[PDB]
Image (tube, rainbow, N blue to C red):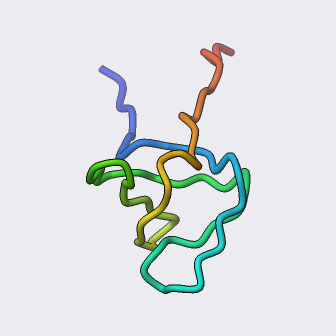
């Protein structure tokens, strides 16, 4: 019954992190980073279809109210 679509962990960038290196994922505060791989402290996030590393200390758990109706 029903079909809920999910994937990775939805996190919000608490602060805008700009990396000069194409290795670290570049995003701004508020952006929605989809975490999938967590290696140590720094986890690998994604955006739409991007990939890179970022400070896990610069991301929060996308908290959304239990929308109902």
* Position in image of residue 19 (x %, y %): 59, 77
**Residue 6 appears left or right of 21:** left
**Quadrant location of the N terminus in the rendered image:** top left
Q: Is residue 66 above or below residue 25?
A: above
* Position in image of residue 26 (x %, y %): 58, 72
**Residue 40 appears left or right of 44:** left
**Quadrant location of the C terminus in the rendered image:** top right
What residue appears at the point 46 percent right and 73 percent down from the top-left corner? 50
Of residue 69 and residue 41, the one placed in the foreground of this image is 41
Q: Is residue 25 above or below residue 44?
A: below
Q: How many marks?
A: 0
Of residue 9 and residue 26, the one placed in the foreground of this image is 26
**Residue 63 appears left or right of 44:** right
**Residue 22 appears left or right of 42:** right
What residue appears at the point 53 percent right and 45 percent down from the top-left corner? 57
* Position in image of residue 15 (x %, y %): 71, 53
Q: Is residue 52 above or below residue 12?
A: below
Q: Is residue 31 above or below residue 57?
A: below
What residue appears at the point 64 percent right and 50 percent down from the top-left corner? 13
């Amino acid at each position: 019954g029903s079909s809920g679509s999910s994937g990775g962990e939805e996190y919000i960038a608490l602060y805008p992190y700009s990396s000069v290196e194409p290795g670290d994922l570049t995003f701004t505060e508020g952006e929605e980073i989809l975490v999938t791989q967590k290696d140590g402290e720094w986890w690998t996030g994604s955006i739409g279809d991007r990939s890179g590393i970022f400070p896990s200390n610069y991301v929060k758990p996308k908290d959304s109210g239990p929308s109902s109706g």
